[PDB]
Image 1 (cartoon, chains in turn cyan, purple):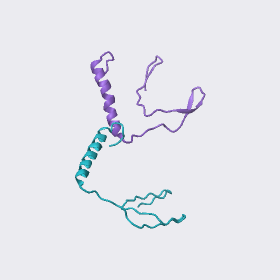
Image 2: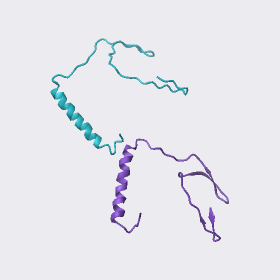
Image 3: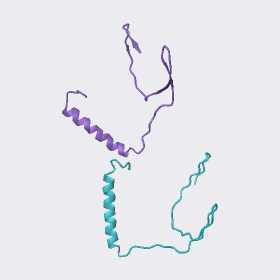
Image 4: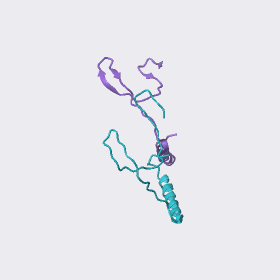
Length: 72
Length: 72
C-alpha cells in the first residue's frame, strides 16, 4: 500500500479464499462469521483437459478477433 | 518571413493543433480570445496499429493502380 496526500487512498488486494455470512449486524459496522467451506475439485480430468484445450482454442480465436476489441 | 512588393506573402508553417474561438472581439483587426486547446492522447494503440495498416493499404493500392491523382 502507498499513501498519497491528495485525499485519494488506493490499495491493492488479492483474493485467497471465500467466506459465508450467517449472523448479520446492522452496519456500520458489519460483522459476520463463516461456518463451513464449500469447494469441489474435478474428477476424471481427461474430459477436463479436453475442455481446457477447447477453452484455449476459443481464447486463441478471440485473440485473432482483437481488431476491434481494444486489447493487446 | 520573405516579402515581395506585390501584396502576396510566402510563409512556411508547421501546425501544432487546432484552435477554437469562444468569444470573438471585433477589430479591426478581428481579435480572438483563445481558450484551452482541444488535445487528444493515444491509449491502447493495439487497435490503432491495425487501423493504420487498414487505412494505409486503401490508398497504397489506389495510387499504385489509379494514377490520375498523381501522388508521390
